[PDB]
Length: 76
Image (cartoon, rainbow, N blue to C red):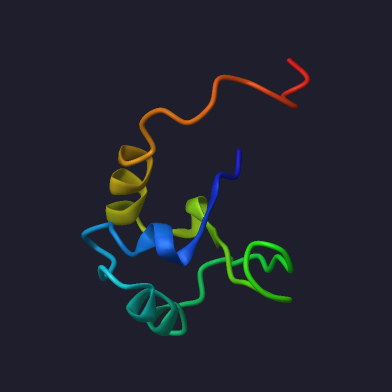
């Protein structure tokens, strides 16, 4: 499993501030396994590994994830 996340998506969990500015700034206070992707924004964005987020965000995370997709590229 992986389920990565984006700063704009973290800017809504309680444990995390309501603005990515605080999440990215706080990201330095720890540095959750964040993968870069030269396509979700600029030549180098900053994703966040959901498994690296604490528990307070892990709970509220999958919470606002209601409805998303059924199954695909999952090779069954």
